[PDB]
Amino acid sequence: VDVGPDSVKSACIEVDIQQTFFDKTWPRPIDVSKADGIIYPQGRTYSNITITYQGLFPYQGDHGDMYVYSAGHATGTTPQKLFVANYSQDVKQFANGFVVRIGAAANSTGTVIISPSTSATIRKIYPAFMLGSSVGNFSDGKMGRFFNHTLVLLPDGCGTLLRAFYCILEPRSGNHCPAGNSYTSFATYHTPATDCSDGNYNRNASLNSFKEYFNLRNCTFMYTYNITEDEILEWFGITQTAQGVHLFSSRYVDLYGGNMFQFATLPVYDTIKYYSIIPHSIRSIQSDRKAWAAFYVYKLQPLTFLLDFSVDGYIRRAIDCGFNDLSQLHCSYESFDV
Amino acid sequence: SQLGNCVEYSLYGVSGRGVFQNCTAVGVRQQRFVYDAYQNLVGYYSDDG
Amino acid sequence: TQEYIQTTIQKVTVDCKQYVCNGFQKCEQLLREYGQFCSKINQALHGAN
Image 1 (cartoon, chains in turn cyan, green, blue):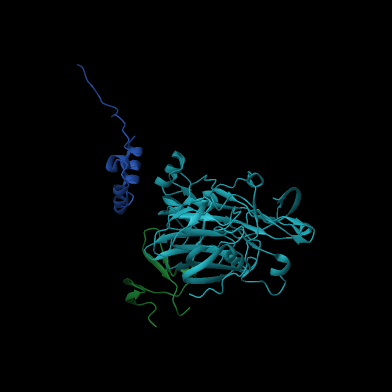
Image 2 (spheres, rainbow over the protein chains, first blue to last red; image 1 turned 45 degrees about the vertical axis):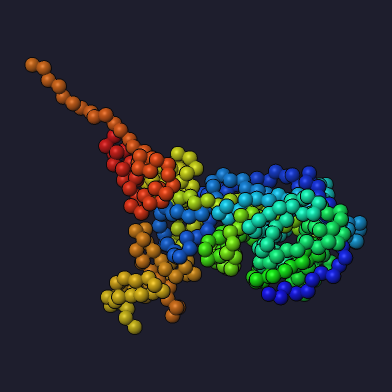
C-alpha cells in the first residue's frame, strides 16, 4: 500500500525527554462496579439479567499505566523543541491486549506539563501506539525499535481520525532521527497554529511527523476511522486472535455509557508481543498551551465477571469474581445482593 | 410473514424452533441476537428493521 | 437405660473448584462447560450446614 511520499526533511525536530515532569500521581483504577474497561460479550446481547461471563477483562483495582502528552517548548509565538516523557523506550509486554481510559480528566482544570505553574482546562487527547513482534535498540543503543512489520495506531487530524497501519519502520538517518546523530526519542507532533484551522484540519499532521523519524516500507494496509469531536470519556481496546487485531471502542455504540464494541479488525497475523506509547508533543505557542488529559492503559486477562445487563443491554455494573472473597460470594450466587 | 406460527429458523447460523412475535426492542441492537439468563435465544433484531 | 440421640452431623464445606481441578486452568476451562456445578455444591452444603 502506497501511504504517500517519504519525508524530505534532512533533520528531525529535537526531542527533550524530561520524565520528572511527567511523573504525576493522578490515579484512576478500574472500578468494575461502574463497569470500567468492559468489552461487551461479542456475539450477542442480553436484557435485564445478571449472569457470569468469561472473557478478557481488566482487574478490579488495577491502576494501569498512566501516560500524559504535553506541549512542546516555545518562545512566544515560535514553537521550538518537542517535550516528551520517556515513553518510546518503555516497551511493555502485550500479552492479551489492553484497554485505555481516554479523556477522563477532560473539563477539569489541569496543568500544562511543561510549565507546572501554568493551569489550563484539560482537553481529551488520543493515545498513539506502536505494536509488534520484536523489539530492540536503535543505532545509539536506546531501546524502542520495532523490527519487521509494526502496527501503528496513530490518531491524526487534531483528534478527528484514527489511522491504523502495518508497515516496516525504517529509521531515518538525519539529525535527531533514530539512525542519525543526537537521537533521544522519536515523537509525533502537530502544530495547532497551522494544523488545526477551524475548517480544514490537517489529516496528515501526525503522520507527517511520524515520517520524519521513520520511512514507511512494505505497508500492507493503512486504514482510517473517523472520530466525531467531543470531550466525552471514552474507552479504547485492543486484542488479538487468529482473525487479526481487534480494535474496540465505546464511541460508536455506547458513547455515554462506556461499554466497548468492536469497530475494526486488522489483518495483522503475526503475534503482537510488545507495545509502546508513541510520545506526542503539541507545538503550541507559549501563550496557547493547553492541558491534555492523561490516558490510562490497563491490561486484560481471562477473568470471570458478574455482568449486570440493563434493559437496553448495556453493562452498567459488574463484579470481578476473583478480586476478593466477597466478590467470589456474589459471583457464586450470580447476584449483586446476597 | 409468519408471526405467531411455529417455524424452524436459521438466522445467520443460529437455529432452532420457535414462534416469532412483534415486540418492543430490548438489548443492544448492534448485537442482533438477544439471549436470556439460561442462554436461550429470546429475541432478534431482523434485517427488515 | 442408656440412649444416644444424634442431633448433629459434622459440618463440611468443599472448595469444589479446587477439589475438581487443583488449580489447573485447562481443567477449569472444561469444568465451566458443566454449568454452575460448584455453585450448586456450595449452596447445597451451605443450606445443609
